[PDB]
Image 1 (cartoon, rainbow, N blue to C red):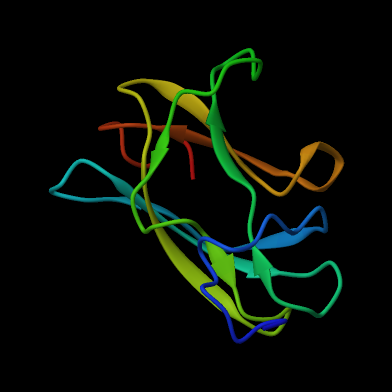
Image 2: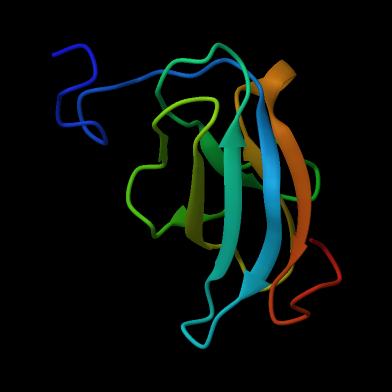
Length: 112
């Protein structure tokens, strides 16, 4: 019930910090693939992921690897993700905890 549950639906969780645990690499599907780790609190997560515009005010991306999750701090998750055709800022965690990392779509390593 706690953790044995429908994980990607039945949670709204981790305000804690995360690691960027592999850099972004783009696909033939035109998506990009992050890999995350949790840090915060040991326990499982669904993980807050957005992509925000250059000013970082407006959400501009769509996550493709379903609703992002991490089974523990010691766990990692590869995440297929769909940014706009330009520069943008993936955010992983909530504000103060958010891994706020650069990307540029089709210029597929000008941000990482």
